[PDB]
Image: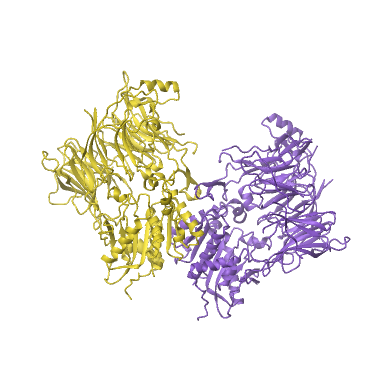
Chain colours: A yellow, B purple
Amino acid sequence: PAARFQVQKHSWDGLRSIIHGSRKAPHDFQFVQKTDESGPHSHRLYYLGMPRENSLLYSEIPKKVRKEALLLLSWKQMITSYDFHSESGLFLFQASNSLFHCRDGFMVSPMKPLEIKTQCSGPRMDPKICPADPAFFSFINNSDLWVANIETGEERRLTFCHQVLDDPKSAGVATFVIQEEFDRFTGYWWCPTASWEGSEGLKTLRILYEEVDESEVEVIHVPSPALEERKTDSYRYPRTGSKNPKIALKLAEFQTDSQGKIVSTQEKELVQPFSSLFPKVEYIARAGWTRDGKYAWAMFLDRPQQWLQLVLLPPALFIPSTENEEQRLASARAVPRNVQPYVVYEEVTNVWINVHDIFYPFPQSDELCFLRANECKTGFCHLYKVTAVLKSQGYDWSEPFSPGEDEFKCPIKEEIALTSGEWEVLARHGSKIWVNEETKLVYFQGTKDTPLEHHLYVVSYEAAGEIVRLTTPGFSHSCSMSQNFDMFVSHYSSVSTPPCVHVYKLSGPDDDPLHKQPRFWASMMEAASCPPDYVPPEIFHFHTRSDVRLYGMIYKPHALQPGKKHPTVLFVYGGPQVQLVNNSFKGIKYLRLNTLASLGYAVVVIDGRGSCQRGLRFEGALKNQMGQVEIEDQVEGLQFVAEKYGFIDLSRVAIHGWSYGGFLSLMGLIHKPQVFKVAIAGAPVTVWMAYDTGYTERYMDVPENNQHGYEAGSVALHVEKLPNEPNRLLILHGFLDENVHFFHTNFLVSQLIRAGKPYQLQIYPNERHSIRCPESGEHYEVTLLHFLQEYLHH
Amino acid sequence: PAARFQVQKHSWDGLRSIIHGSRKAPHDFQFVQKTDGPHSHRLYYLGMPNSLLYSEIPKKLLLSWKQMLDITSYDFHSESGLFLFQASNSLFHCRDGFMVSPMKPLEIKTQCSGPRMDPKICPADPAFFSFINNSDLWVANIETGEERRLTFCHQGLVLDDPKSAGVATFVIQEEFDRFTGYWWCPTASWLKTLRILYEEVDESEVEVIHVPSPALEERKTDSYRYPRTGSKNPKIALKLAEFQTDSQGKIVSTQEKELVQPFSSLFPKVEYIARAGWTRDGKYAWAMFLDRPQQWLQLVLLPPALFIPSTENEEQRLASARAVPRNVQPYVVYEEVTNVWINVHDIFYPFPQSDELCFLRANECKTGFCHLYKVTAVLKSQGYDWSEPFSPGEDEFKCPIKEEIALTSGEWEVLARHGSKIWVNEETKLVYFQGTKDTPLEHHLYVVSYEAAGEIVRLTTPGFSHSCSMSQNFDMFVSHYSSVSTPPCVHVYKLSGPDDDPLHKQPRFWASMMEAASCPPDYVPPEIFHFHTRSDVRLYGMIYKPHALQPGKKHPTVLFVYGGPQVQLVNNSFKGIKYLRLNTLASLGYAVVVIDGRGSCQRGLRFEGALKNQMGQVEIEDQVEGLQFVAEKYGFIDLSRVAIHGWSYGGFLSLMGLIHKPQVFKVAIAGAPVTVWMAYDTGYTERYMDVPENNQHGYEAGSVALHVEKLPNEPNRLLILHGFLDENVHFFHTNFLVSQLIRAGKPYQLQIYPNERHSIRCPESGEHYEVTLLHFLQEYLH
């Protein structure tokens, strides 16, 4: 009868004004101690925030608090990233199209940023202060590594692998598939210490860097942002099965005198080619140095991404690069048989290695003690104290050799578990740990309390004992520690409450540092006013028929009258490396879901199997079958919501999602036509044989080994099982999308025409993957409202 | 009143079976004589069940389409009976004793990497034949197999390799309809040397734009040189490629030959080489030169002796510069000036000499109507020192014209554009030609004497548009003729009668080759009409009446539009092959109106010239004036429900109509629309719309994407179709319009044809387009 709820239909200009209507935080922290204890302030907080548009700001922390009274802090003025040197108070930051610096006695009010000059050509990307001497700093220029000296003003080039498609070589740069899939955004690493090699005079500074050759990498053309010019940009995009770049790790020594001038520069290659010491190493995932600089290190993945290994590389293993086959052998004979690369840690899986950023090697007294995160051992990411034996087996470096299985594999002396259980230590997505050697405590975030909340915990690396939570529960926290471990910040929020940024002081007796109370100290930002119509979503949980727990959000139809069945937008992603259902504010990222709710739509969200923050075997439901598992968990999760809450009309379900969610949306419409009446597919993956290697191979093997899997999970190949009926499929895509190439939309549209199927299509000519410009976003949300308003019926 | 007609609303699979229901022509004729003898002549031509076919013409019913072979175009050489053509991506040949059963196509071997484009036989000696390969001019020998490269403008990289010889550039092919950049000399000189005129071209300073490749899978773009209106056109020059051959048929020596003074100093203000060739005696090479404005044209004669061998030795060159006689000189033999634009006309037939030069030339500038002229020209050598560098201008080489007769006159045109041609019988002193003398709605065959502008006799029978080709011996002609109601036939006609009265030789039907094949059983043809505007200017329209009509019912109307220059949709020829979908649109009960408004073709230059500098503005007001008349004369138009539709200019005119006249048009379906004239090329735009620096106001006003704010705020009033691979009207236009629509908060709907360029060629794309068109109108034209 009048059981069904019909949404108030609006005019276009009405829908536009409803969406314009619904549009009406600090980060990148550095703690510094004051060390003038006759004044009112104990610390200084440097950070990045928009007072509008991003900039560098400081705040003063007082010694005595306001007692029983909440204390805000003024954001005092003085830019996506910056580098900092705590020993000298020197800030280096890429701003405008150049580089800028500034010092911090402690300044009163803003100082003007002194610009660093250059005789280099283009922009100076990826700048870093030399930790060993803050007189120096590095940068990339035209795909090559440079070094410069702020004081004297002297720039020098250190690599020469570059001068378009006849220039595939490049040094100190992270290739595309490393940036987008392995989340590394540099390919050079400062040696933290400064050796004094030779006989008399000079100080040697070293830089580890990734040399790279993208010749055999397939080229593809994405349209140029400047649409007027009608040109394209070339991309070294390797597709699944095709060849990744040829890689190598290489050294860059350069000596400098006392008066601060650069004397000698020198490229250095591995004594035996990278590819011969490490056959079956495909991607350098991460790299760095040990605290003392005794060994530079890297994490090497194999192509099927089922085999990680941390390896040390002593500088001594590096000889000067020359083309003289004669000369090469001399320096090769000059390398002692002691010196060698030591493969320390090794992670093997039947699923896939997720890269984990956590690796803290301890200085040596012979052996090597270090902290490592490891999700392959128990199926859940946990800290471990690993000791490894560096025993030199004595190599002749002048004659070549093939390594044999575990050639450089170190004997493990001990390997302690510092955490355990079916939760995980946050180790991907920029999550870092903080180690205090004064007290032998290690600070980490994790899901210990619940998957839906990120929390700060401390544990001792001496004794794997009591783990103390420091963040207050009922919220999810992103945390940053002080270097002095006396204070920490938390950027936190909840489904109901917008984000705040509080400063805390760890307080109490020092003879028990584990059990230091986290006392609230001062606030950096209090919860902003909720949007006028913002009712928060309600998190629920249910069990699949296979007895495996699943979490879901729901956005209640605002002003609900029980007994009325509402039409339901199911919002989806349901792909790896993501969690949509967690106890943190969603209003900034997803108010569209609220806007939908407010016009009387049910908006369900469901983290099906194959999503983040549930350990490995959960993520592993995907393995070699993308599309074939995730959609059943959505149906179940939707059906459950229809039983628990009474307001879901199942006759009118609208699956909508972006990227993998765009992919799932179409898969939903294909495999479950009687369930979902309409699909809205945003920037969908339509053909997996077209997507890139790092991502696709990791989850779906290579097309040769997973023929049946690639084809079944490619929606363009199954277009005949899309609706014969119009107004059941809306495709949205950003022309300029460099992750999911427009080709996918294009190829699907080509396939729909051959199978005689109808479709609506929308294009974002200036947007890429993420819709950035407001106007484009408004138009997107209005099209969504309008499409559902006319078509989500029957 | 419940007199509003509602079209039967179908399911999609329903609409699809209606469009699949719907879908359920020889050219390039060459006459040869048998000179024996049961058969007289023999027709050679192209055709499908696409390749070479022949028909045996009797001495005394339909004709048998025989086969030659075991193909777009061929070259033929009557003397040797040699056929050269481009089947596959290779080259083949064959001779026509006079064969009874089909012989095999003999293949030509090659050293060359890529394909062999633009193949032509040497007229002087059929043993030889030329071709382009990696944009350079090559010469081969069918008999020996010996190949030889003449021009050396290409390396092996692109974008660093801009120069090229013997090729027609982009704007030259798509806006001047010249498809070759070389021309054989039809004679030889004596060992014997064989000349070729060719265009060397430098596209160094032409703006590069990228376009997606047909192979979407590889994901790579092609790089064109597309010069946008206001930007630089290619640097060009005419050149001579000579080569000697000994008696055995070997190439013993070649030679690049530049003009003794650089091309840009001899002929300043020349931007494009529209056409070129030679006189029948090979005495003079000739070219038609335009200026960037395209309001100035001159026909030039280049004597070979004005060409000197290329060398870096600037003393050796000076040696040659001295050796070119002061007599020899370029002769500007004709000049066409105008305040509107110079349409390029193919008709130029010089008579052989033995100081005078007689020639026939089509001229539209003179009287505003394209007509044949007999022109005697004084070639009086002025004397020049070619050793001294000098800069002439304007009328240095301008010849005195001694006579200028008009062989035709009357507010109609002689057809001379897009490969229309005259046939000249020098024996009978008659020039056969095509024309609109009887009516603009039909293309008839006429003869006049080139001696005296006397009686013009018509040969083709009235009621039908005709396309004809004459026997080289002016005894017979074919006519590919059709009409609105009747599909195309191909009839063969014999010019019988007294030889002592040639002008009045009567065309007497001899034999048929093709007979009008039955229409798709649901086909009811359109009917032509005319009306006058408020300016009392006559316009022609077609209409497709709603099938099975009930008088007193007003039907929903689809105004189909082009309205752009160089085109005429309304005339008396069968439209139910290319425009079958308009009949389907009728068969569902839509009225479909087509109106050739001002700016359109076949009504002379001032009717076309209404567009000048105002593209968009003049065109819609005419389309409405028609539409309004249509509703009054035929009482079945529901004006409340009129859709607009069109491709290219017609997409541009739908978007204009929905901007300038929303009260009239409820919807627009714009296909491959030109949304920014400032983005379009020089060839087209600069002609009609001047240059952006000059006509700022007119460019802005005619760009439908600078006026998006005035598009509908209602959804379902605008559908944008576009071929992703369109190389004429780049997808960018759609892209730019979509970006402008989003800024302004305006709804659109988009259909992409990812494998189609400007025209939809693939059947499935075409069916989907016609199903989407029908679905869109069924739901939203209400």
* Residue B505 image-quadrant placement: bottom right
Nearest the eye: B260 or B24: B24
Residue A194 is left or right of residue B337, and the answer is left
Residue A418 vs A190, above or below: the answer is: below
Q: Please count the marks in the image.
A: 0
Q: How far from the left and from the top, in percent, is residue B545?
A: 60, 73
Question: Does the image show residue A454?
Answer: yes
Residue B553 vs B183, above or below: the answer is: below
Residue B20 vs B316, above or below: the answer is: below
Residue A425 is left or right of residue B758, and the answer is left
Residue B109 vs B498, above or below: the answer is: above
Residue A287 is left or right of residue A487, and the answer is right
Q: Residue furthest top?
A: A199
Q: How far from the left and from the top, in percent, is residue A595?
A: 33, 62
Quadrant placement of the C terminus of chain A: bottom left
Nearest the eye: B430 or A707: A707
Residue B433 is left or right of residue A512, and the answer is right
Q: How far from the left and from the top, in percent, is residue B127?
A: 75, 42
Quadrant placement of the N terminus of chain A: bottom left
Question: Does the image show residue B407?
Answer: no
Q: How far from the left and from the top, in percent, is residue B612?
A: 61, 59
Nearest the eye: A714 or B362: A714
* Residue B491 image-quadrant placement: bottom right
